[PDB]
Image 1 (cartoon, rainbow, N blue to C red):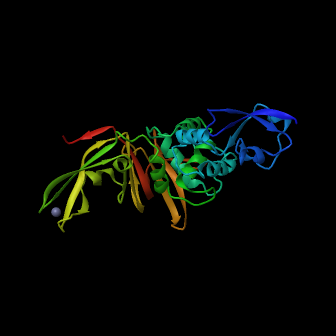
Image 2: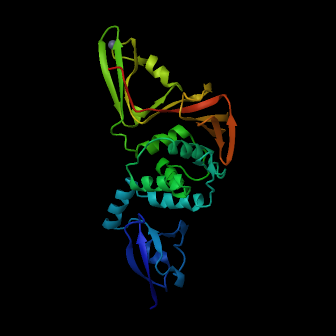
Image 3: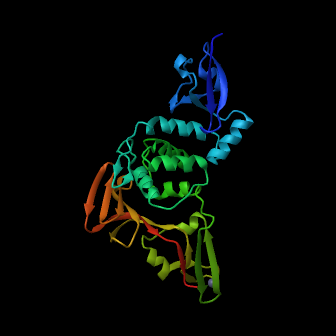
Length: 312
Ligand SMILES: [Zn+2]
């Protein structure tokens, strides 16, 4: 009975020493097993695997609690879906475009590089160590893990088309937004004044208009009385906000926003590209950069810098 010593893990931090029988496959001893993203379930150990670290599924109490602590998901197929995505994203290219980590086009991933590009420009911290650690590696240029996690957390697979806003919604559920607050003043002609306070993801996102200012000037609201009142922004406490709408012609001017996403083509199969604002306007389209004086185009999401906003 020849054996070699390896480590199993669900989080790449807690390592569990194992003696593996070289007579049997990894799958017979650990269940489904992965090495650096590749499925090694069907193969028997090699000599050179001595001391390597293998991902396995959470199959006992210790692994399940380490997996929850690391991923904060309570979906049991998560790690397998993560690994299956990572088998692809590890073969993607993450070039520096405009000082940011982008993604070379592959597997219909253009919506994902827009997500990735936007997140590097926001001041955001993630509640799940898996996301926080991969986020750090992504901004340094090794974003394969971060992309695969974004897919797994969004219940999307490699090669599916996607929506930036829907993707950001899932990610920000694992962001630390407990201090994020949005105060909306609502008053009907009939029932008087009321203060709605949004927190968390709903404090930083809005669907319906691309303009942060249109939230200050007023949005129409249903009321339990029966009439239509008006609410608007009296207080915002967050490091950013994200304004979204169906694709509409929008002017983007330097100094007035943080970054944005353009969407061209059909709803069934379109093309996202990232617009950011530095010394001039940048368009980041996968690995391709274009600088521009002005911009007017089909925009679906605009991000704005924020800190503390009050009308007291
Ligand atoms: Zn009313």
